[PDB]
Image (cartoon, rainbow over all chains, first blue to last red; front, side, top):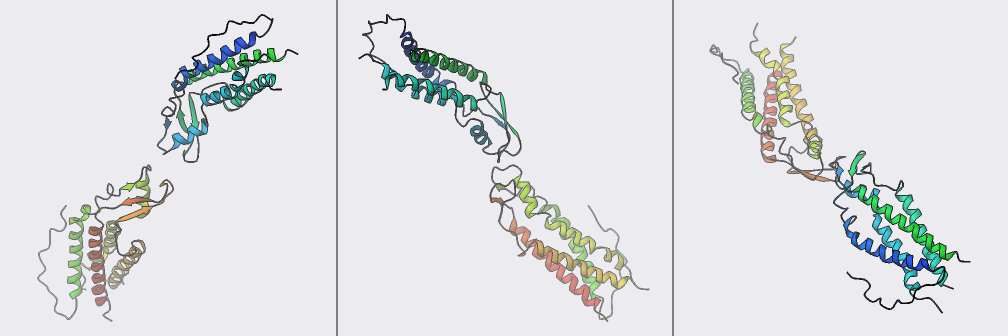
Length: 176
Length: 176
């Protein structure tokens, strides 16, 4: 891939005691894109052949995999970014009803993804072994995970990023 | 093995217009012993590793094997013989309440084994493929058999033998 190949005329800088946010926020935008693609198919890209189930039950790997991973972290992120992406191309150029409502959209989205995330991954963690007692899964069986530490780390990162994103997003939203 | 190694003094033969049965019946006794041991562990002796089940279900071979073969033919025979065996050593020597009741026992046993047999192997046959839909056997699966023709043949034999056994057994039971 390659994303962004024309940014040369940016001599105009800020002078006020504000609009520091847009710097921080474009930086976090670009950042999160890199951070994503660089580790995109490279942490969670694997986790299909990595959910070993101690059994001889047919299918129970698939069963428990959806049971505990309806969706992977990186998708909720990918979405979180895209919904939080549309205000970016908006704020690309501003001076001359929406504009600040773009800022607010950007806030509330990111908030939503945080909440529903912690609803799903309660404990902000990756259990080393998830058991499973699904229908075909004849009793409570065991179902492993690879690299739970890893995924936990990058999750801590992205959530911290979400917090700072919103804090400057809102710190300039709160101009009154 | 070796069974029977002392029979020399049998010069006394029958002269009446009866007791032909005891000849026929001792012959059928000895016969069925040979017939058994010669093919004993040699037709049904195999059928443990011979009940292939098209599946990947664990255990479903054992499951369906008991399902369709609670017990093998040769056991019902083995029993049929033994219950029908005790009157033999009785009638070994006779001239001088039981004696004829031994004959009747010998009849009714053999009859019973015939009936319950056909209850179990209905159709006097060996199906080339028995399906199976047991609990672990996830859907209706297939479960093969080896040498069904063979076993069918020797079954036809033993049942015919049962018929003639009883017919002479009773033909001399019916003396009045």
